[PDB]
Length: 406
Ligand SMILES: OC[C@H]1O[C@H](O[C@H]2O[C@H](CO)[C@@H](O)[C@H](O)[C@H]2O)[C@H](O)[C@@H](O)[C@@H]1O
Image (cartoon, rainbow, N blue to C red; front, side):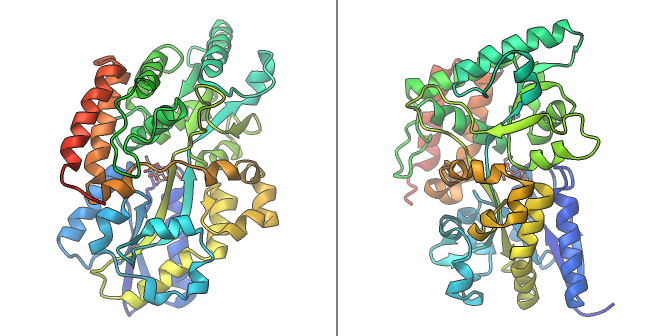
C-alpha cells in the first residue's frame, strides 16, 4: 500500500519466540491502523544489540522508528529517545509499575514505555526431585549442589551421557553480569556498585560467591557453560538434560509447548541463597519501547508503542510467551493466572528483584558491565580466584567511574 513505513527493531528471532511474536504484533498494529510496517531483526545478546543500535543512533538514522530497549539502557540511550511524557496522561502512565517508569525516566525525559519485566528464577525438574527422594527445591546453594551431585550420579548411571545438574549463563556477555549479581547478592556480597556509588564488590562474600560458581564448572554444570547464553542453557534443560536451570520466565512457556520433552515435569522458584539470612536474589531485567529521536514519523511511532504496551498485547505476551507484564492489573487477570499460576506465587520475588548498577553507572553502564562479566568469567574459566577477581574488578570499576557522578 502507501503512506509512512514504520520500521521496528526489537527482540531477536534467535531467542525463543520473542522475535517472531514481536513481528506478529507489529504486523497486527499495521493491519489494524492501515499502516505499512517492517521488522528489523537483531542479534541474540543484548550487548550486541546495543552496539548494532548505536550504529543507527550515531548516524541519526531515520531507518528505524521504534526500538525495544533493555532496562539497563535508558541512561545510555536517552539522547536518542523521543520524550514520551507529553504523549501520555498521568492516568495512562500510572497503569505501569512506578519503579519501571522511574527507571525509564532520565533527567525528566520518559525515554520509553515499560513493555515486559524480567527476573532471574530457578527452574527445577520435579519428576527428578521426586525420583531421588527430595520434596522441595533447594533453598541454599549448598542444597542445590548436593541435589545436583546425587541426581547426576544416578542419571549418568542410568545411561544419560548428556545429563547435568545445573545450567546457567556463563558466556562473557551481559547475561553473565545478571547471573553474577544474583550469586554475589545471594551470598550477602552486595550489589557490585551500590546505588550510592560505593564500589563494594571487593569483599569476602562476593569472592566466595564467585569461587562457588567456579566450582560448578565441569562438575555439576557442563564445561561448556562458560560459552552459554540464555538459549544454550535453555536447550540443555529443554531436552531433559539438566536438573536445574537459572533463566528468565520466557523459558516456562517454551518448556510447556507440545513436543517439549519436559512438558509437565518442572516448576519454578526463587534462586537459592547462601544462608537463611542472606537476601533473595533475582536480577531485574526487562524491555521498554522507545520512539527514535530520529524517526520521521513520531506520531505514528508513538501510536505503535502505546499499542504494544497495551493491556491486551501484554496479556498475549504473558499467556503465550510467559513474559512478565509491566501492568499490575494483569497479575490479577483470571486468564493470565490460570495459564501462569506461578506469576502469583513469585510476584514478591519479581517485586524485590535486584537491579544491576545501571542507574548509578548511567551512560557508562556498558563499560562497567563488561568489566564485571570479564572478571567473573575469569573465575569461571579457572584463570583467577574470586579474591583476586573482586580486587581486580574493584580497580577496573574505579577507573571507569572516576569522575562520574549520578
Ligand atoms: O525475557 C527473555 C529475554 O532474555 C533476554 O533479556 C534478558 O536477559 C538480558 C541479559 O542477557 C538482560 O539484560 C535483560 O534485561 C533480560 O530481559 C533477551 O535479550 C530478550 O530478547 C529476551 O526477551
